[PDB]
Image 1 (cartoon, rainbow over the protein chains, first blue to last red):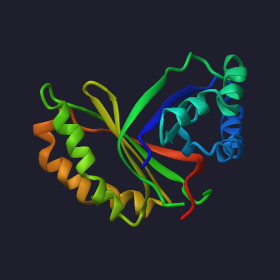
Image 2 (image 1 turned 60 degrees about the vertical axis):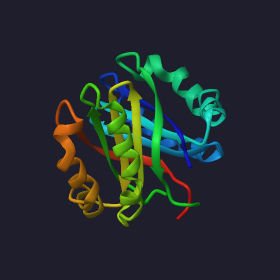
Image 3 (image 1 turned 60 degrees about the horizontal axis):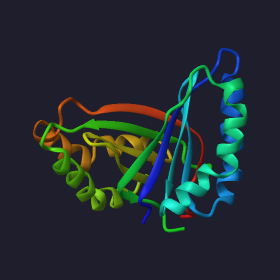
Image 4 (image 1 turned 45 degrees about the vertical axis):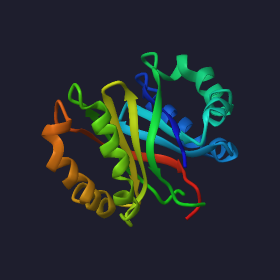
Length: 101
Length: 103
């Protein structure tokens, strides 16, 4: 079972809403490449408010994601894309249902 | 898969003294989620001492609505006053992209 997760809410700068949505959608292959990243979701709450939820078997998986390509790419573009600094929330998974793979 | 497109992001605030009870409630709800054929992924969340949640994902509106009207929602509604300091905060979410294990 997946036991650990991360959640981040992301607010787009005026004029960078498409750019942020496209960035998040484009990261899917990067998430598929991360074997320790069990599940990964690019979220849209509203026209300028986006986010990511992802899930891991263990802390090694979670840290590998934070040290990985998607987190890197987001940090490299954050100042361009985002209107406020995002808080990456650590989450404990109390239970999870996923397809078996 | 690109085929899961909708989600809910729910925050739940535990009543003081009820934090363990809410965590336990959520964990015991797993079999109920497992049985929901339209609920592709379902995660019971703990953010902090008294702050919990659910993130769940669906192929379509029918699956999302079946969850909102399902056994977990009913159980939480039956016990809401015992466990929660305010009503669930439920956000409808669109998925731009999603990785799940296959199946």
